[PDB]
Length: 34
Image (tube, rainbow, N blue to C red):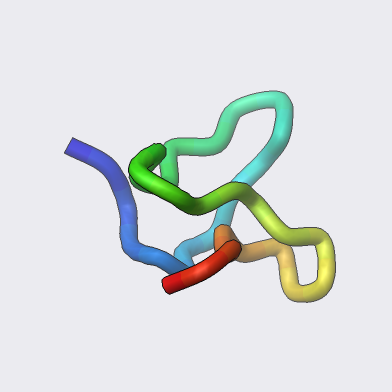
């Protein structure tokens, strides 16, 4: 199970779904395509 396409995250300990997303420093949340 993972988080959403825009949940808090950390490149040293994130958990956003990995189907097509990645943490984003822009707001400290995970994002990428959708």
